[PDB]
Length: 212
Length: 197
Ligand SMILES: [Fe+3]
Ligand SMILES: [Mg+2]
Ligand SMILES: [Mg+2]
Image 1 (tube, rainbow over the protein chains, first blue to last red):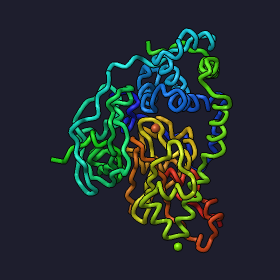
Image 2: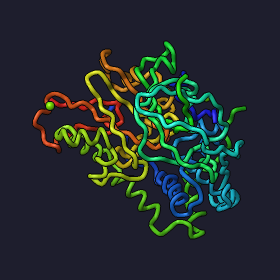
Image 3: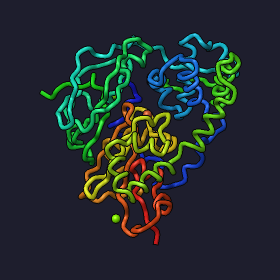
Image 4: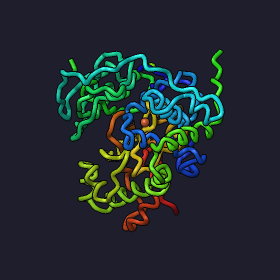
């Protein structure tokens, strides 16, 4: 999904709000902040109601301006709440009644997702690959900066995981795939407009194809 | 035009979500409190620091950490949620590694701790993949011009830690002494370990 969450390479932001080794304060800065992750895990591990992938996608589905003005941990409150409503566990009524006011949720999905691809290639360390030039309206773990770009394989994972584009929508056809550390030259991604060396993206097999 | 939606205070929303679930019997007793404790007390960059210090003082373990990071971490019992498949990335005299999650916040929680606010910022997520040298400079870390910067974007299940170079002036230090200078920011990659005078 080509959402505003796909931030890498966006220009116009100011300084990162940190200097190295500065005090970051406590893990949680407010008494509710442990709730989003805890309740995510309740949903995943205890209820079996959704995957972590579905959490990532439901946050991507926040209305874009809402996403942009919402602090991090609040986005996951919104996202977990949304999934609990969508899965029929909770109602928005009861959430707003208990909150004592408005509790807007992420927007409905506009895609049913897609299955794990049936045709993929097992790549080897040192191989050259291209990121498939595809557009996925639902969830995908491919930042747009690397779409259609060429890099080289630095690692093939020894484990395999469900294809995000499927389980992120709660589908039954996510299969399993390894992922690959794909090393791109900075100039491949941003031309002359970068001060970097290389960028390594951890890409599902189904996002990749052999380079020409 | 472009206005924020009306929202109840975030604390009220967050506790409403808890209460709605808990009042249906969906949240075990002590569940969120247990996670709170894990996140605050167990998941910690002191663990990654221990790992770095061991690698610095034990060539065999270094090799293991760089080849099968998951197995290395498991020896210490530090695998966990968001830290199941570990890759350690080695800094060298010509290479500085830095980690981000441009899409969200993904971080090797058990060994780095939960990410700090700045790591999750839009500024870091947008900028470090494109201009890491300037980002690190602004943060207080000057990377000599003879060093390639490599940014790892944590886009799948690999969870990364940086193995920084060991600074001069630490020769013969104990593992405890070395661990003290390997900070959270060293593990993320935005800082280089510092030796006092
Ligand atoms: Fe993330
Ligand atoms: Mg975009
Ligand atoms: Mg030495």
